[PDB]
Length: 282
Ligand SMILES: [Ca+2]
Ligand SMILES: [Ca+2]
Ligand SMILES: [Ca+2]
Image (cartoon, rainbow, N blue to C red; front, top):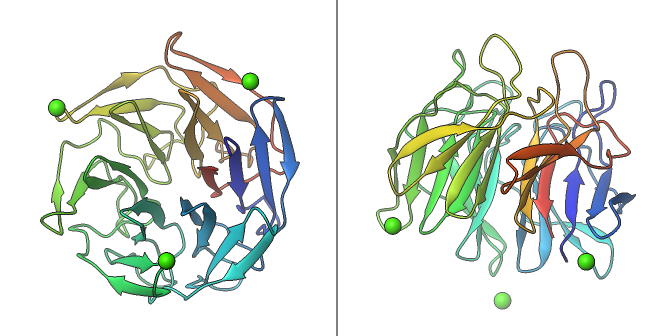
């Protein structure tokens, strides 16, 4: 449907159940049906033409609940809950399944990983990561899921792991040049883009890109704004960075990276400021 969906987050006072969608044809945001549950630190993905919002924090607990938006009915419906409560988890989709990666359960930072089967409406565990990671960024590239950065309970991480769906286990790949917790992670062309985050000292406007052909990370032009708790997605050959936290304020601004001009430019802001939001393209 070629729209960017911005899901939940925290606006500085409220944990949001609000959802809005960006139309690139008109450069405008409009609101969507709100979720059943408030969710900051939420993970979101699209599976068989529906948007899933998994985990997060509702203002009182970390969540194992998971809800599913159908664009036709404009309704959010709960599906089976995750086995682990997870805020600041990563969420992605591979081979018809949703993968919930890491996160924080209210006491522990998780290395556990669970997969959702929409045909049986059940979650199952898969291989845990080598490293515990909340505030992790995930994405899929070819036959693998990548988990980059995050926070292991005491350190912000620059390490990066790859889940090979054939070997069914996680292995380390080249680390990021910067440590990044609460970063955004997305895939463009054949590369993984790591966007923003927090390095233990400041909130980052920097960006770097992973080439699987060479197992190396390289510099890309930084964004105009520092953003941890940012959501990122690709739409029509451009990368969008929406929301986050610049070190002082939750953000409603949105920037778009053009790969030709290597330039970030602001587009229309969202109606709500959202740190620790989910962002996906539907
Ligand atoms: Ca057009
Ligand atoms: Ca089916
Ligand atoms: Ca190759």
